[PDB]
Image (tube, helix red, strand yellow):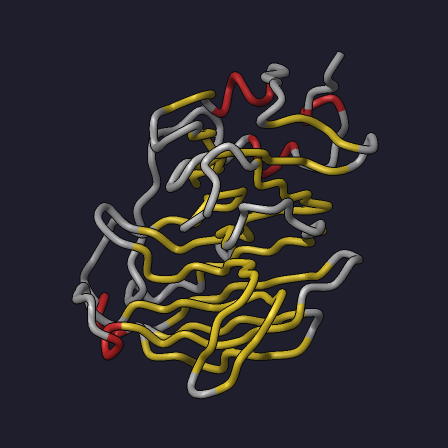
Length: 230
């Protein structure tokens, strides 16, 4: 049988501050249900250690969505609210099976768009450089479709072992730290000033696969939203 993520202590803080969406944006488990032992093949404890997310199908997800703590409703914050908003993780991205091409593993998202996606991607060129098997940042600076609406960059090549991430937003600026090194340094998020529906996400959100039956799989060794107001 499958062991529940809440059976160990590691993820209890974030599970108290998240709902699970699966296999679409539809609610799969409330925070209370997650803390109470919700489990399935999509969301279970791997190796007695890892919060593991699995999903197949283009645009499908198994993904935590930040909530107000202690059974609260959906959080919404703003890049320009003056508070530092912080998400941390330690992620083991295994080798993805054939047909899986891109898996979004952390986001900043609002009512209608992703401010930021951190994703594993099999192969993509960025700014005239080809990259394979790597972790990418995709920041929106507009809601249009042309390249001017995005800042897309290489964060790090995928590692077999755990990789630490930290996302910080303060005063309309984004910093992403990977394995303790700042990689994105104060990216401008001021396009989003006044959007008060932002929140963190993390898990597995499957993008542009070439097989809808192929299962994306992501293991979290740690995940938290860090409250600077205690």
